[PDB]
Amino acid sequence: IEKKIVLRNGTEAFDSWEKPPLPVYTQFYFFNVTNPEEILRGETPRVEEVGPYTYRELRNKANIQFGDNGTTISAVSNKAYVFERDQSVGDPKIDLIRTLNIPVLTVIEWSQVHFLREIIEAMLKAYQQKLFVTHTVDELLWGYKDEILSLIHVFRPDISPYFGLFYEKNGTNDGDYVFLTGEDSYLNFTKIVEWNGKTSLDWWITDKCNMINGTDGDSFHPLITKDEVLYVFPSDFCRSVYITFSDYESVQGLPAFRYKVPAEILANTSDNAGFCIPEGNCLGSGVLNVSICKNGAPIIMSFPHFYQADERFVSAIEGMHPNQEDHETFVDINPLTGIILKAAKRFQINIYVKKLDDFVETGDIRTMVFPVMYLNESVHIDKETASRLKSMIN
Ligand SMILES: *[C@@H]1O[C@H](CO)[C@@H](O[C@@H]2O[C@H](CO)[C@@H](O[C@@H]3O[C@H](CO[C@H]4O[C@H](CO[C@H]5O[C@H](CO)[C@@H](O)[C@H](O)[C@@H]5O[C@H]5O[C@H](CO)[C@@H](O)[C@H](O)[C@@H]5O)[C@@H](O)[C@H](O[C@H]5O[C@H](CO)[C@@H](O)[C@H](O)[C@@H]5O[C@H]5O[C@H](CO)[C@@H](O)[C@H](O)[C@@H]5O)[C@@H]4O)[C@@H](O)[C@H](O[C@H]4O[C@H](CO)[C@@H](O)[C@H](O)[C@@H]4O)[C@@H]3O)[C@H](O)[C@H]2NC(C)=O)[C@H](O)[C@H]1NC(C)=O
Ligand SMILES: *[C@@H]1O[C@H](CO)[C@@H](O[C@@H]2O[C@H](CO)[C@@H](O[C@@H]3O[C@H](CO[C@H]4O[C@H](CO)[C@@H](O)[C@H](O)[C@@H]4O)[C@@H](O)[C@H](O[C@H]4O[C@H](CO)[C@@H](O)[C@H](O)[C@@H]4O)[C@@H]3O)[C@H](O)[C@H]2NC(C)=O)[C@H](O)[C@H]1NC(C)=O
Ligand SMILES: *[C@@H]1O[C@H](CO)[C@@H](O[C@@H]2O[C@H](CO)[C@@H](O[C@@H]3O[C@H](CO)[C@@H](O)[C@H](O[C@H]4O[C@H](CO)[C@@H](O)[C@H](O)[C@@H]4O)[C@@H]3O)[C@H](O)[C@H]2NC(C)=O)[C@H](O)[C@H]1NC(C)=O
Ligand SMILES: *[C@@H]1O[C@H](CO)[C@@H](O[C@@H]2O[C@H](CO)[C@@H](O)[C@H](O)[C@H]2NC(C)=O)[C@H](O)[C@H]1NC(C)=O
Ligand SMILES: *[C@@H]1O[C@H](CO)[C@@H](O[C@@H]2O[C@H](CO)[C@@H](O)[C@H](O)[C@H]2NC(C)=O)[C@H](O)[C@H]1NC(C)=O
Ligand SMILES: *[C@@H]1O[C@H](CO)[C@@H](O)[C@H](O)[C@H]1NC(C)=O
Ligand SMILES: *[C@@H]1O[C@H](CO)[C@@H](O)[C@H](O)[C@H]1NC(C)=O
Ligand SMILES: *[C@@H]1O[C@H](CO)[C@@H](O)[C@H](O)[C@H]1NC(C)=O
């Protein structure tokens, strides 16, 4: 019965893997900074939440190649974002948001450790730059031209003048994956054996932290059980995470197990100590330093409103109001199929900010992990895809 779900050009699992039937949505949430100058002079930051802005993902797998014997498959996954205005607050082309000036914050990082050179820091003093900027929502995620980057682009053309959170992530696959089909065992269904041609991460300080575990997270192995733990590799998150069983749900007419991301994942603990790039020093519970993943930028990952995290971070930034129900990330999956009936996946992007004497752009600013944006990656099972799926046996 389990044999029905494998990835091979005959099965229905494949056609639904190749072109996933269910629509998937990402909603974007920005924190609009209230007191920019007051922040620079050392006062507590205060933000206002702005969102969502709704984009429907267009998902198909490409460059599908076939296994050693029958046991492996490899491909890339192209996701594109199609904006839905009526499910969003406004038109992100018009709508404005004020936050940290991120492009300059990285080159400043690039000043202190030299990923490009210090002393071309000159461009910073030649052209006045602000640590807080205003750009349309469309601009921050889909890209805009920065004036510092534009100059630096002249001396070294490899660096792009364009900054964006999601810049050039429309329509493109991340990474080359090779995947384990269900032939050796169902348990290995859509497991990640290797990514980008390397089967491990080189980013993290220990052997265990650097492992690539489990599925990409958009599917699971059939015949799931309440006791076990499901590993997931979120490429964009720069590491692998697992989920623990929470409660029993009924989506549609069908059973589901609710798995959640346990607070342990981003917490400060001796198992997690490798996620500190300096070793013996990491920032604390509930935040991760994802810098090496992103071009040397001082970018911190956290859950929305710093949920599942030390509350000293929550205190530092006004307007952070973490609650479980909204900011948790959960997966409701069908025990038999392992198919995902409903889920919501939520990460937050933070930027590390501190006063530097070498740069007056930073003023007297407090040392803190500063919220820019978080997102809900969500999926719900349609009511006629429910019953065709509920048509089993056979
Ligand atoms: C989130 O996560 C991020 C990563 O994911 C974190 O990012 C990390 O942040 C830490 C913060 O501490 C940072 O560590 C620092 O690194 C500094 C940079 O190190 C490199 O550069 C220096 C200096 O470059 C200059 O080197 C000499 C001159 O000093 C010259 O010969 C060089 O060519 C170059 O000079 C050139 O430029 C000038 C112009 O400026 C020209 O005029 C000149 O002609 C030259 O062209 C180097 O010394 C370093 O070398 C080390 O590392 C390489 C790696 O390959 C080794 O090969 C090398 O042997 C050496 O290794 C060891 O020596 C250093 C000696 O400083 C020791 O620190 C250590 O034992 C090394 O293992 C690098 O090439 C660095 O300067 C700084 O250290 C300073 O402060 C400490 C304070 O204790 C002092 O003791 C030192 O003496 C230094 O003054 C510190 O180590 C990481 O680099 C950074 N990593 C990444 C990947 O980003 C981020 O922090 C995190 N965020 C949060 C919030 O947690
Ligand atoms: C993707 O992720 C985002 C963010 O997590 C979700 O957006 C949230 O959606 C939830 C519902 O799924 C919203 O929750 C509702 O908020 C309403 C507004 O509450 C305000 O008003 C009350 C007092 O009236 C204040 O106390 C509060 O602080 C707010 O200022 C509530 O009225 C709703 O309450 C109803 O449901 C709850 C359920 O617990 C009951 O307790 C209530 O009695 C009542 O029945 C509810 O709390 C939330 O506001 C949304 N937030 C944002 C930022 O948009 C998306 O839903 C999620 N999924 C998708 C598909 O987008
Ligand atoms: C996030 O916070 C920032 C900072 O508070 C905020 O940016 C500001 O938005 C307001 C609009 O909400 C901008 O004010 C407008 O500026 C233009 C250009 O000068 C004017 O034409 C506008 O005047 C009209 O405004 C009303 C109608 O729109 C009328 O009452 C009025 O008579 C005029 O017709 C208006 O003054 C302001 O320029 C920006 N400020 C900065 C620094 O960007 C942003 O809107 C916030 N985002 C969200 C989603 O709330
Ligand atoms: C991301 O790329 C996709 C793919 O082109 C865009 O989706 C299309 O957008 C056009 C509007 O220019 C419309 O025809 C539809 O919304 C999409 N086309 C089809 C055939 O579905 C999407 O607009 C792009 N988004 C951004 C932010 O660049
Ligand atoms: C990847 O998976 C391996 C095992 O599947 C994890 O290693 C285990 O970590 C736990 C920590 O509680 C230890 O008790 C086990 O002894 C470890 N097992 C093995 C075989 O090493 C590893 O931590 C996972 N890493 C990531 C990043 O998900
Ligand atoms: C699956 O369907 C037929 C089988 O020959 C073929 O036209 C198609 O290219 C196959 N696809 C893959 C990825 O093998
Ligand atoms: C696939 O087969 C079984 C199922 O878990 C296991 O013993 C084996 O190690 C799996 N292969 C890989 C590469 O994980
Ligand atoms: C992280 O944990 C270790 C051991 O539990 C502790 O020594 C260190 O102070 C902690 N740091 C933070 C920021 O919580």
Image: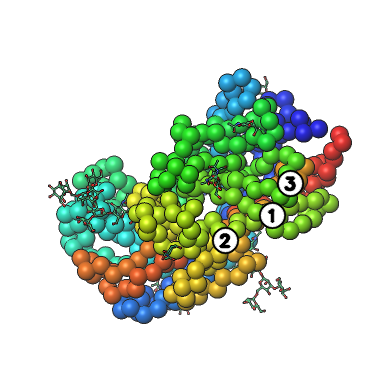
136 sits to left or right of 77: left
How far, Cα to Cα, is label 1 from label 2?
A: 13 Å
Tell me which image quadrant ligand 3 sits in. bottom left
82 or 328, which is in the foreground?
328
184 or 169, which is in the foreground?
184
Q: Is residue 94 visible?
A: no
Label 3 belongs to which residue? Answer: 225
Q: Which image quadrant for residue 61? A: top right
Secondary element type, mark 1: strand
Spot occupied by residue 279 in the image (x, y as percentages of width and height): 36, 54
Amino acid tagged 1: Phe
Estimate how packed mark 3 is, as few (under 14), some (14 to 19) or many (20 or more) residues with alpha carbons within 10 Å. some
How far, Cα to Cα, is label 2 from label 3?
A: 21 Å
Spot occupied by residue 169 in the image (x, y as percentages of width and height): 47, 46
Q: Which mark is residue 245?
A: 1
How far, Cα to Cα, is label 1 from label 3?
A: 9 Å
Q: Which mark is residue 220?
A: none
Spot occupied by residue 140 in the image (x, y as percentages of width and height): 43, 58
Tell which circle, 1 or 3, labels the residue nearer the N-terminal end.
Answer: 3
For image coordinates 25% across by 67% down, the residue present is 356
Amino acid tagged 3: Thr
Q: Is mark 1 within 8 Å of ligand 5?
A: no
Q: Is residue 243 visible?
A: yes
For image coordinates 53% across by 61% down, the residue present is 303
The way the protein has been coloured in the rendering is rainbow
Amino acid tagged 2: Ala
For image coordinates 70% across by 33% down, the residue present is 186
Label 2 belongs to which residue? Answer: 263
For image coordinates 77% across by 31% down, the residue present is 4
Q: The C terminus lies in which quarter of the figure?
A: top right
Tell which circle, 1 or 2, labels the residue nearer the N-terminal end.
Answer: 1
